[PDB]
Amino acid sequence: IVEGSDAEIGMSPWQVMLFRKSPQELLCGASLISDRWVLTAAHCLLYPPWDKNFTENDLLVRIGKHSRTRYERNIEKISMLEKIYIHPRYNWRENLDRDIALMKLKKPVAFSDYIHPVCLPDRETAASLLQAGYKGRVTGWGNLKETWTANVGKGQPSVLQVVNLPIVERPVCKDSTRIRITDNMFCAGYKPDEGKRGDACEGDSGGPFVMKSPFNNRWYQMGIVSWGEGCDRDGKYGFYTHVFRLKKWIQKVIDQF
Amino acid sequence: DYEPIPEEAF
Amino acid sequence: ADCGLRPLFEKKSLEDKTERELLESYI
Image (cartoon, rainbow over all chains, first blue to last red; front, top):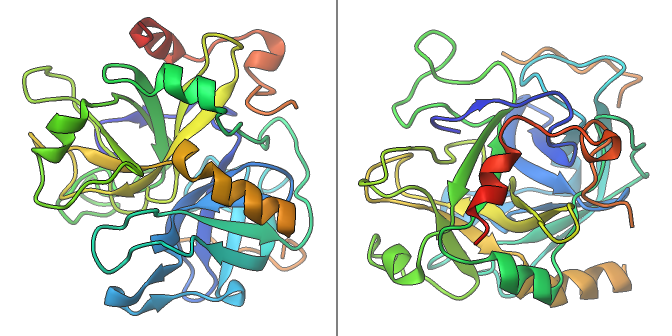
């Protein structure tokens, strides 16, 4: 996350870290939607252009975390993947259309003060909140800057980062890039005139874009960190998978498996 | 730079 | 059924430091 701030403890209890077993590294963010289902971006698991095609045993998910690098004893829980399900029409060849995947856990993770699921939007909540100007929240352990940096030149965070960003009008999203945008995507971020900044960055993808419903005070995951060009560049916006638009697939997978 | 995940935890 | 209600925030009626920014943007 670029230009965000440290998350408060228990602020994003549905946050999940997708961790490569060997070599141990942060691959992506993800979100907890029930005790046995984790939601993420399909490109976190499958992206042929980069020779990426993970299998269940290549990965581990860490839930309940705050610190990026530390093993958080008595707090975080490790869960293993029983099965990965990628949207059948995920378009990795062109524009990451339908960038969504589900991971079923081998055993249910135990909820606690630091582990709790986020809700998925119903049609009405999505129609009401997914509007230009309305802000959502992005969280992750990704890089703090576009310019390749680590723990020596303000590169990676010590703890979970958070940033609130406004959804952008679709024509403005379209006009900011040469990539073909689809209805299964929305973009968010501040414009150059607005002053405030912020964006997701390397390592944040797969993570959640959430909104707190003013109708029932519950947090809903409206998007999945999908793609961008650079990080926090003026005139560019982060792109997110439209979760409600792909919910039929989500429901089909969960009901079936 | 990741602290190792102790067995038992897995 | 208990989704989206955080143990350390909504569950105990505590607000985090920037959630108001989201509410203010809705409308």
